[PDB]
Length: 294
Length: 108
Image 1 (spheres, chains in turn blue, brown):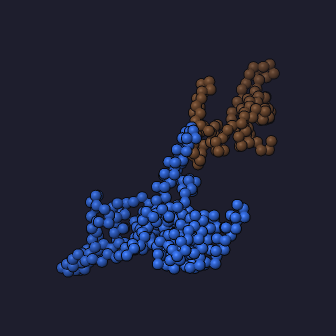
Image 2 (cartoon, helix red, strand yellow):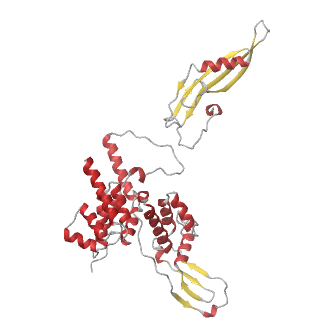
Image 3 (cartoon, helix red, strand yellow):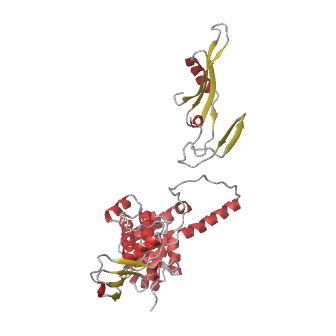
C-alpha cells in the first residue's frame, strides 16, 4: 500500500514551508519584554547581505513547525491489586521516578489507590507531576483558564490566534486532547472569518494547512492565496491535496490531463472543491488583472 | 512663543557694596527654555528685583536656542562623557521606558 504522507515527510515539509512564506519583519517582530540599549555596527553591502543571510537562517529555525500527532490513548494498566491495604488509606498516593536521565515518556509514575490497587498514572496525572518536578518555562502545573471556550473567543476577536497557539504549545503536549481541541478550534475560526494572514510567516501555518487538507476544506485558503497574488502557493496546496488524497476524483483528473500550474487549481474547482464557483471567479479575476496590467 | 516653557535652575540673592544702600542688593537668575521638541536654551538674567531678573533671563534665552539631536525622539544618539571645568557629566543612551535617571537639574 502506498504510504500515507506524513507531516514530517521531506516533501510535505517543503510544500508547507513554501506556502507559509518568510518575512523577516514578522518573524522578528519586537518582543514586549525588558529592553537593553541597542548595539551598532558599521557594515558594507557585502557584510549587510551576510547579516541578512544569517537572519534568514535564524528565521528558518524560528519557523520550525511543532509536531502534529494523533491523540494519545488512555493509560489503563493495573500493576497489582493488594487488597490487604483496602481501607487503610483515604487518599491516593502518587509515586514518581525522578531520575534525571530518563525521557519523560519512559518514566514510571504509579498510583496506589485506597482500595490497594497499584496502577499506572493517567496522562493527566503524568503531565501534572512532571511539571512539579521538572518544571518547564511557560508551563503551569494546573491547566490555565485562558483555554476555556469563552476566553478563547475573546482572543480570537482581538486577532490573537498565534498567541493562543503559542500558549497551547507551552502548556499542553502535542498528542493530548486539550492540545488538539485548542488547535482545531483556532484553525476553524481562522477559516470561518478568512484570517489566514494572521498565521503566515509563523510556525503555525503548516499545521493549519495540514488540518484543512485532511479535512477537505482548502477552498478558503486557495481563494485567499489567489486574491493575495500568491498563486504559486495555491498550486502547491493543490499538489498537497492531490498527494494526501491520491484516489480522489481531483487527483485522478490531474493525471488524466497532466495538469500543471494554474491548471491544477482549475481541475480542483470542477472536481472536489466545496465552493468551486468562487475559486474560478477569483482565479479568473487574478488572470484578468495580470493580463490586463501586464 | 506659547510653545516654549521656561524653568528656573538657580536663583542667587547676592549683595555688593554700593553707596545707594551701602550694601546693594542683586538677584542673579539662571533659567532654561525649551519647546520639548529639540530646541532649548539657557541664559542668566541679573537685576535688583527678582521679577526683572526673570524677564531678562527668560527673553535672553530665546535668542540662544540650541537644537539637540534625539535618537528616535526619546534619547541621545550615543554615550556622552565630558568635563566642563571641574564638573564631570556622564550620559548614557537607554532604551524606551527607562525614564530620566539623572541629576534633578538634568531632568528639568
